[PDB]
Length: 237
Length: 184
Length: 53
Image 1 (cartoon, rainbow over the protein chains, first blue to last red):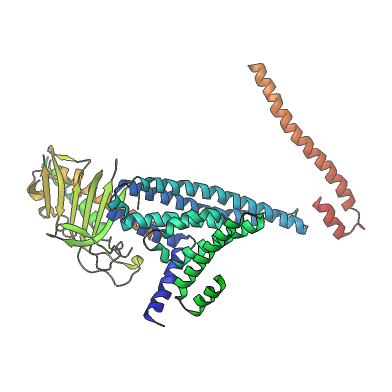
Image 2: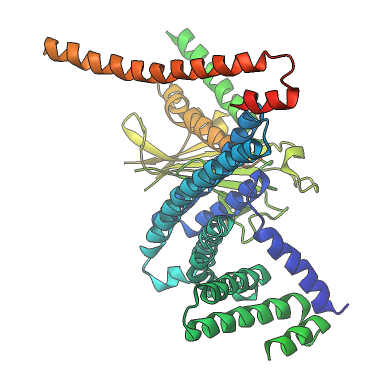
């Protein structure tokens, strides 16, 4: 490969890791680095913004622990009224909706905290401070967890304004997952217009934006005028 | 009488020694917070009494830890300066202690009074040596003039380590420990 | 107020009882079904349907 392709391979793997579903090792790593930003920045409103973000992520992490425990407790019940196929599926349908609805509540509590993290960053008014890598990386991590919290529950239209705000920050536009999620969420919205028989202007708007971020994600991961790019070029025509 | 004073000083010398032996362990944080606690990684710099935070907080050549404590303003600061380089291994669970070359602390808020004066800066230049290292502790006095703890009459000398220095060493060791364990 | 407490108690007690009327009508149905189940020529497959009920 070229020196740029080798570098690119390394970077795409780092970006995929960056957007990894949360776990305990990533939690620790994240709060090491987000605190590293608190170190240089020395700003009480940034500290408060991070304190709220961390409370939001803790909501998510505590929920993941709840979901395993709940499923465990259900599995460990003796199911003597389960002699039918429908009754097994019934109890499955009980599990899935209780788990999904509990995750929906955890999502709101996490987003109320993320909203507070943003409201505190909004109070940093000095443009010399808002342009700091410390300000931008925290704002990026708040948006990323926000995007993922909604994405997991299939709330894809809601991810668009946050992905768009995300890619505007400090070269986030060069992140392959950011364009992959934008393209997928736009695809969903295109499909909604096709299923609900909505207006053509919105059909084409959503289709266009899907193709822009499909093409850009492809360009970023494989390189422009690669067999993989050239393929997307002809399809978008 | 003077007997009780002698025993008290000895207990305090050992109290600062045991915590300095714990503080020398915070090397484990170089390859690595509780609320309102801010830790910096860096290197000894300037005149050798202050710690300069790294551009690269993760850097393997950091030999100083600088810890700031906030509450409701900056209340306290500590700088742990270590002798020796860090282990090559990137995993902090494997890292070993390094005797401290110096401990520098600052009190900004919640100031203690020793004979009605504030010692705002304490500079320990032999934290892992003989517990009886009062001649190695510089005291910077505000009402900041330099005094040596060993030249402090004694109660006074005892109040210094009992009220100011041991407590700060213990407060910071506990904060460094919370930082380490939380991220380890 | 003591008279009221006595009456509020009546409602607690009646609420509880109504759930137990439900429970006993259930047992009576279970007994009916158990008798069918106790029929030694009533098959195991058919017992599965009854035992679900």
